Amino acid sequence: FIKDGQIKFPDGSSIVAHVERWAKVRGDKLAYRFLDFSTERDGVPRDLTWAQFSARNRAVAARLQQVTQPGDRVAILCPQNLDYLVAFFGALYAGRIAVPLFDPSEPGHVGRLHAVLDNCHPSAILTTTEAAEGVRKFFRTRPANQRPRVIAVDAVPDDVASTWVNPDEPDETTIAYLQYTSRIPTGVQITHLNLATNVVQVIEALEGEEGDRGLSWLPFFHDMGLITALLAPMIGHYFTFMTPAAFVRRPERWIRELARKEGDTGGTISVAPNFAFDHAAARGVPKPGSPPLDLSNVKAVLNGSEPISAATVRRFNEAFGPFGFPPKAIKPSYGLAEATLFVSTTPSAEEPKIITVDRDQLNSGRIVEVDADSPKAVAQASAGKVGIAEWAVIVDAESATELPDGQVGEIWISGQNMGTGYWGKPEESVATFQNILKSRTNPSHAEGATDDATWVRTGDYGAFYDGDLYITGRVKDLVIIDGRNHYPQDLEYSAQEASKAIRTGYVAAFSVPANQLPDEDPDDTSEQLVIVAERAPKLDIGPITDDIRAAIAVRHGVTVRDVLLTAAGAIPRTSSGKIGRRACRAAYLDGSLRAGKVANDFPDATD
Ligand SMILES: Nc1ncnc2c1ncn2[C@@H]1O[C@H](COS(=O)(=O)NC(=O)CCCCCCCCCCOc2ccccc2)[C@@H](O)[C@H]1O
Image 1 (cartoon, rainbow, N blue to C red):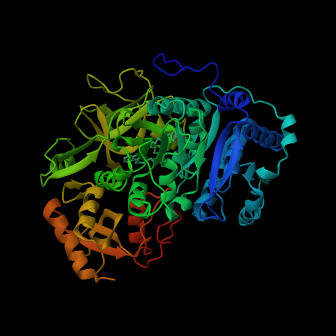
Image 2 (tube, rainbow, N blue to C red):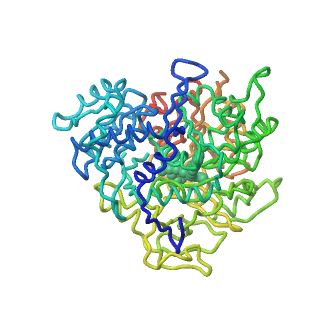
Image 3 (cartoon, rainbow, N blue to C red):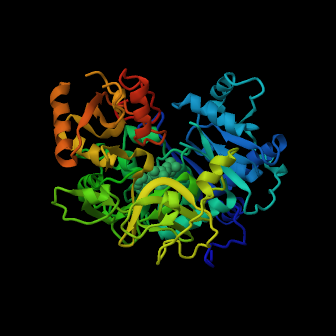
């Protein structure tokens, strides 16, 4: 669609009308393929053509229109499979607000599911026949008046579709679905306009052509897995997916989906968080004597949702370069739920941009390049260029003032893809989404946005440098000790490089007040460094601790006051698998981390 400063639609912005059209001209073509690895090690493909997809969406939608009213929320408590997509699109087809969640009988934070439900109060629950009893059982733990009707989407017959009524065309405020992140849970209001805008933004950035195909193992309950699933079939080829557990168990599965197949006229496109690249590199290489592996066909594998490590990038290429994997296929990318999904990515024709900058300058808020062999060198991966019809600026948050390039400040963003608020929360909505950019530089990274445009504060620090956006970390994760700043991922890299006994990527650095440290001055409240590190899957703690302490002291000039070593799987991670530093700190302070009793729901390599 055309651009006039912003993205214009009419013919419509409804994904419903667009899928229905796309469906009538490619009826027999495949739309989705689910690789089910639950009973068979090599997988069993479950296919869905466009005509079947449409038929099911219309049937589920008609059923929803009989038992829910316009404006009601419809929660999806379903495992990762074809039915999850049918349930989600069914909600959109019905003109009801979907709430993509997960199957309560699978791993999950049960207290958060209760909190989410306490905020969105759905009028219906969409699940499958297999998951239904488990869903009901969960609702028997909720109050008697909060047990909405449970619909098994695979049991709604196709003929129920005859009564389906295409909902009223959406305006710019009409909410399509709520995206819960990540306690207290905030549901981002994603409008049909938001969704269609980000879809167009992503398609422009990916430069997908006839024959390219998309694939993913990412969970549908997270923005990166959901949005990818909704838009991948739109590039012209069916979308293939598997579960996260399936990937974690045998990462080679992802690698072989990416690889060239007979019949491929284009390349493959996927997306994953940074830790997944390391898991694939260490455990996803074919064993000698396996069928040939040709990865020279990969077009783009986006690396986003968490900090990109230059070492992870190097390890991925070292493992898969010998199989033809082109290094320019790795595309560091940035985004967040409040922006639907996509904010920036490395241009299609370019290789990842990775620079080595001065540590001290970085810690004091400035990007200054240095030689890679310098002892003060910190490697920073770029997140590329901001997408079309959206803007990102770097600001001094308190004065809402843009900063010149090379200076670090909070990243604020704007665009038609920004969510319209958080469900039921006016104060939080204003604070996060309705910020005003009071002062701009010349040139301004806000050029093209109106002076009264609203800005979302991302909670991230970053900077522009030589035409690329760099994400340095979350504001709330910064380590401030004795008047100096330290990025926790830089301290973590030093800790793991100091000892082979630490699992790569499973380290968390944060500060706690002096008085919260263990017994090994009760009025001292100054922030002190703590390193939590998982042990590689037993060597005594003394030598390891001293290696960590000594390496951090020499290059960062800060003394670790406590090094806590845990078993693999002990550090808290979000539901999409990101190391959660604030959560690790809270577990350190509330007694659960030291007692070795932290609950994690994302599948772990060991268990
Ligand atoms: N690059 C980065 N570096 C450091 N931190 C990053 C980060 N990206 C996100 N984060 C951190 O994650 C936070 C947001 O978390 S979140 O709400 O859970 N949301 C997220 O994590 C969303 C991240 C989205 C990243 C952009 C990915 C766009 C993928 C399009 C692929 O399309 C396809 C794929 C296949 C076929 C066809 C098309 C952010 O606020 C930031 O703190």
